Image (cartoon, rainbow, N blue to C red; front, side):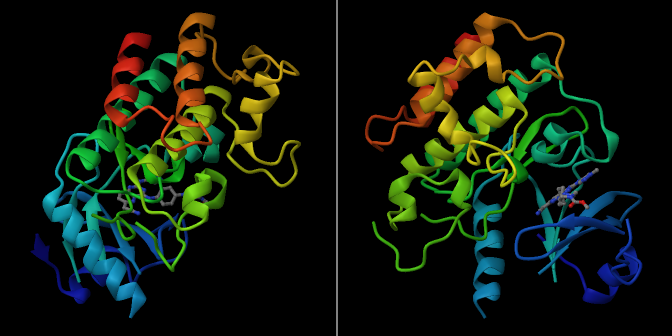
Length: 268
Ligand SMILES: COC(=O)N1CCN([C@H]2CC[C@H](Nc3nc(Nc4cnn(C)c4)nc4ccc(CC#N)nc34)CC2)CC1
């Protein structure tokens, strides 16, 4: 990768100008809009934080794929800019963007499954799969980001986003089966347009919807995001059946990523 000087980065981000050059937060840092080589970039300004820095670089060096973000360099971490932001924000229509159609959602879901597959083929565990870590390019192609906590098993330091974590990950296990569970939560956000956790909602956690539907108190049709005009029952049910399989409480009963990839392909 290229090694930028801090001064060059400070220049391209206008002193790391906090008004909306600031794009938002971010992993364990803030994201700034940059311009280097007439080329628009994302500059993320971050001892344990140095470990996440080195691990991002370490994984980005090994893993290059059409469904993963691209690190250009460091000082700060510099990436190729994703003009369509996070899936989280596009799902919430933040800053007035239009709602994603079912057609776009299917390509996104497939793309995300492809990124996760590459990671798992390369013996990497993300540990924080969520819609905020799925970015969207100039074609709305899904790209997985934030590898500061990725690992090549039990841990004493429990990391991740509670609302997306598998029960074994909340207890400390480190397994690729946990990424599958989180992805299943992401599929629910895609179907419903609802964030994984809303303190001002009942149920507060999205994952509690599998049970409602599962214990026939609910229909998946009741939850289908109403901000689409092109959803069809068959593909939505087929995407819901994948999410439901990913979300098995038992890590071993979950499909593997290669299976998730194939089922989403059979969906379209
Ligand atoms: C007030 O606004 C809020 O609260 N939010 C609104 C912004 N949200 C985030 C959206 C994604 C953003 N990261 C990134 N973004 C963009 N492009 C982009 C973002 N928006 N747009 C319109 C275009 N390219 C990137 C390239 C590489 C990396 C590597 C990392 N990490 N990251 C990003 C962080 C901020 C948080 C909630």
